[PDB]
Amino acid sequence: TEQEDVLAKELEDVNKWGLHVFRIAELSGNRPLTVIMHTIFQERDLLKTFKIPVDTLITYLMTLEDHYHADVAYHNNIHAADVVQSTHVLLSTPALEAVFTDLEILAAIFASAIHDVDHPGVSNQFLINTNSELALMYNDSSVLENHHLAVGFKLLQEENCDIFQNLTKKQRQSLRKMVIDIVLATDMSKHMNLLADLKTMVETKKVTSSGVLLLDNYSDRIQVLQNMVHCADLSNPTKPLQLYRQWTDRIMEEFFRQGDRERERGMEISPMCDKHNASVEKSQVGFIDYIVHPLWETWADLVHPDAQDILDTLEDNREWYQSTIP
Amino acid sequence: QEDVLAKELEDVNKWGLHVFRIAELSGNRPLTVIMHTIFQERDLLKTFKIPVDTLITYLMTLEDHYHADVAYHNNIHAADVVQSTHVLLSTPALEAVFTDLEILAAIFASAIHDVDHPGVSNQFLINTNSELALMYNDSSVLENHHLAVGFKLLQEENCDIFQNLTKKQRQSLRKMVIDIVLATDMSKHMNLLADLKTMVETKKVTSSGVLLLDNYSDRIQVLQNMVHCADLSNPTKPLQLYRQWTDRIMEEFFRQGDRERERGMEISPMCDKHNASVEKSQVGFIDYIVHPLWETWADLVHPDAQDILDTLEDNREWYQSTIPQ
Ligand SMILES: COc1cc(C[C@H]2C(=O)OC[C@@H]2Cc2ccc(OC)c(OC)c2)ccc1O
Ligand SMILES: COc1cc(C[C@H]2C(=O)OC[C@@H]2Cc2ccc(OC)c(OC)c2)ccc1O
Ligand SMILES: [Mg+2]
Ligand SMILES: [Mg+2]
Ligand SMILES: [Zn+2]
Ligand SMILES: [Zn+2]
């Protein structure tokens, strides 16, 4: 119960950017997704709101967590827990106070939890180019993301796993649609289109008399949730450096293992996946400059000035990686 | 009785092929015999080095994955859509538009476009929480499944009709086939029609009247609308054919409505056998869907679709006359 006390203390940071998610994974016995989701559901009163039995929540979360691969270095249950917790912090931003309903909040957190389930540790392009069964099933289109949704939803049908058993039919239908719309938007090939649309929304943004974002139709509401989860998914370089560097080590391992499979198959090796011709530091600076900072600066504009500290951390971490190059 | 079948197959280039007769005379293999005939007529076996035995083995296996107990979405419909696409690809206004790989993709897409169809709609599959809708996240559920089956069957023994295509050819063909079949999702009708109207408004032609389509986006949109028109071509056929298609779709609709009734769900439009108006539904279908679509097609290929449009308007007038005052 001493370990349990230490875990509880660490979970006190669940509302903070920079939670010690790797320490939570160890202290929880490799159940970071289960314990962070349960803590967040308690913090947001979601079990009471949606009449979710606690044993059903825990059973589902444990089964979902089991369907992340413990043998992939990056796209595992720790990444899922991190994206869940990051989405939870973004949802609490002052610019969004009272903007989303409880069902939308539930959808965004559930989408984050399932968004990479059963990820094999290789990209959509690799699955397409190797004629995989997954790419055959999904017609080369959002292959991974369609699979993560189908698994996340199928698991609700296992014994004592239907956490949505007490929602109305209309609530379940709406939640299902929003979860699909959010996870499909995490397909990395959609990033540019998603950001272009977010930029349009910032350029045209409306704020209520209370100072919060005005979102008066489904398209705008879902677009904000899609970009929120995509920011959470691309949040590693915005975290304190000791967390960011562990994420870099993990993604590089997954990339290099994919590159080794590509090399052995005589395929051209994907960018950043050739361990014999890699520049990890240049690759992080490029990732920040071309992808992560454009996205996060736009998100920070949407919610100005709420995300200023996050953006400042991203910029400091860019400067740090750059300083290692010369 | 291969002589009568060969005679019937001599009409493979004509709108109004006796496809039901062919289905009967071929021992319920219209898809195989019509695909084979078209591949010969277009010299596709030589062009793509397709071994004839592989072609037949694949076609028979694909045909077997259409359900024999579904009245409309079966192998006869697949064969009809194939042959209708084959005729549309020969529209004079489209001469020189499409490459041989694009022709191959449109015909293969038509052949597979409804394979393994269970005889119920996407909305039925979604609202019944079916395994198919769970797999495909409620999005083009049937059409994703038809593509996955159609491609998976190429992996059966002696079924890889594309074995001698180059690697780039196979990649391009696969993408085009996916783009075409997913566009056959009926819920996309208005979007496709909009694309088609835009292409008509901005159409570039030679001084002969031949369409010039420079970019892939425009050409795939033409092929999407072409296969969609073929899919929605029953009311533009000779009336004796059209009336058989109406009988078949109504049987399939009513069976869906019977399953819906027994499961106590709301019965979909046209699916309630105790409350149906078959003839009014056909006139409505032509007025709101098939005629707008085919008139826009006819504008795109003006004036080469005028006989097809003529037949459609004749058949509309006939069905209207069957509705009493
Ligand atoms: C959307 O843009 C990109 C997407 C991708 C593929 C993504 C994926 O599939 O899993 C994660 C990958 C994003 C990523 C996360 C953490 C990183 O470092 C900690 C990192 O380093 C390069 C890259 C690569 C490069 C891109 O530019
Ligand atoms: C795109 O618009 C619609 C689509 C649909 C659903 C389609 C489908 O899934 O299978 C075939 C159906 C089209 C169809 C074909 C032949 C017909 O009669 C010979 C017919 O009669 C009503 C309707 C129904 C109504 C529509 O208006
Ligand atoms: Mg993902
Ligand atoms: Mg279809
Ligand atoms: Zn992810
Ligand atoms: Zn069809």
Image (tube, coloured by chain):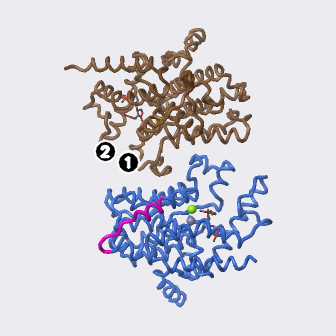
Chain colours: A blue, B brown
Q: Residue at x 67, y 54 (%)?
A: A126
Q: Which mark is residue B265?
A: 2
The 10 Å Cα crowd at callout 2, few under 14, some 14 to 19, many 20 or more, is some
Mark 2 vs 1: CB contact within 8 A: yes
Q: Residue furthest left?
A: B325
User: Percent from the top left, x then y, of residue A103?
Assistant: 36, 65
- CA distance separating discs 2 and 1: 9 Å
Taking the image as four quarters, which one is ligand 5 found in?
A: bottom right
State the residue in front, A322 or A132.
A322
Q: Is residue B296 above or below residue A117?
A: above
The 10 Å Cα crowd at callout 1, few under 14, some 14 to 19, many 20 or more, is few
The local secondary structure at tag 2 comes to: loop
Q: Residue at x 57, y 76 (%)?
A: A238
| Tag 1 residue | B127
User: Percent from the top left, x then y, of residue B175?
Assistant: 61, 42
Give the residue type that dot 2 points to.
Met
Q: Residue furthest bottom?
A: A2
Give the residue type that dot 1 points to.
Asn
User: Percent from the top left, x then y, of residue B57?
Assistant: 66, 29
| Residue B29 visible in the current orientation | no
Q: Quadrant of the C terminus of chain A?
A: bottom right
Q: Is residue A205 magenta?
A: yes
Q: Residue at x 62, y 55 (%)?
A: A124
User: Percent from the top left, x then y, of residue B188?
Assistant: 44, 41
Q: Is residue A8 magenta?
A: no
Q: Which mark is residue A150?
A: none
Which comes before the other along the chain, label 2 or label 1?
1
State the residue in front, A215 or A164.
A215
Chain identity of mark 1: B
The local secondary structure at tag 1 comes to: helix
Q: Quadrant of residue A29?
A: bottom right
The stretch of residues the image draws in magenta is: A197-210
